[PDB]
Length: 5
Length: 233
Image (tube, rainbow over all chains, first blue to last red; front, side, top):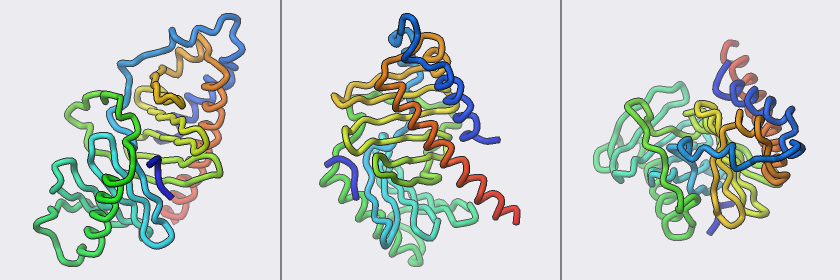
């Protein structure tokens, strides 16, 4: 649910 | 006609030419680093279940496309706010002075801002963006969607960005430059003029991604057409 962490 | 139909024309022409099958692929000749974009999406958070899609642009501005189709943008000054109603009116507010009616949304934008800052890498951190002129205002997120393989982000300046989940490769397509920037798995980046890719060809990796990009742009265009039909009643 998010871009690369 | 719009940014999207121009982009579709550009992609159709390069793709029809089968660029990876050229007698001598000269991919490097198609590079045009001058046409690097001014803006792209460097971070995003999909809170669409409940609230919306939050994102960071490469200039460190942030924005949100809320589920109710309103938008809030926070400039990289950390204080100037632009709010856009469903019907398009922009209001110019600030984090320090704004209507209490927007408390909940401004609080949501701060949540996204802080989450992205704590946890997420900046895409294209190694890229110096192009300098925008007089009219190159901060764009916002016109629409987006996700597939099994990618998130598709369409900005109000016409750019379409496709980030691939599996291998972290990314495309940034601009219908004004008629160009594509490809960020590979090593985070190396190249920008290409689409007409030069048609002339000189390219590798299988890039060619496959451009075929996917065309499919995605057809999807964007069909949605846009649908919402315009509804809007014109």
